[PDB]
Image: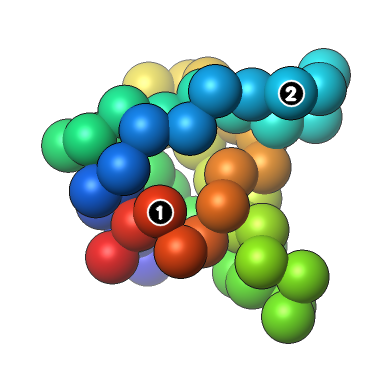
Amino acid sequence: GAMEAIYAYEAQGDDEISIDPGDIITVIRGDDGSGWTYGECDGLKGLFPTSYCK
């Protein structure tokens, strides 16, 4: 499955990825209640905030 970024996020840690509006992000591990999804966009992989996407 995938998510589309609707807000920008700037990573704050080596395990996070920056996303920009319009990014299509493939979900690897969905949100487990933490507010973070683990996924990949054009091979960039890491955690990003679920609520910044749809």
- Could you tell which of marks 1 and 2 lies nearer the N-terminus? 2
Q: What element carries label 2?
A: loop
Residue at 17 percent across and 37 percent down: it is: 22
Question: Vertically, is 30 above or below 17?
Answer: below
Percent x, y for residue 49?
Answer: 56, 52
Q: Which amino acid does label 2 sit on?
A: Gln
- Is residue 32 left or right of 52 when viewed as pictured? right
Image quadrant where one finds the C terminus: bottom left
Q: Name the residue under label 2.
A: 12
CA gap, disc 1 to disc 2?
15 Å
Query: Does residue 53 appear to the left or right of 18 in the view shown?
Result: left
At horizontal 37% and vertical 33% (from top left) the residue drawn is 8
Q: How crowded is mark 2: few (under 14 residues within 10 Å), some or many (20 or more)?
A: few
Does residue 47 show up?
yes
Count of labels in the image? 2
Q: From where the camera sits, is residue 28 visible?
A: no
What percent of the width, then of the height, locates residue 1? 37, 66
Q: Do the residues labelled 1 and 2 touch (CB within 8 Å)?
A: no
Q: In this view, does 4 lie to the left or right of 29?
A: left
Tag shown at residue 52: 1
Q: Which residue lies furthest to the bottom in this view?
A: 33
Residue 1's disc number: none
User: At x 31% / y 28%, what residue is drawn?
Assistant: 20
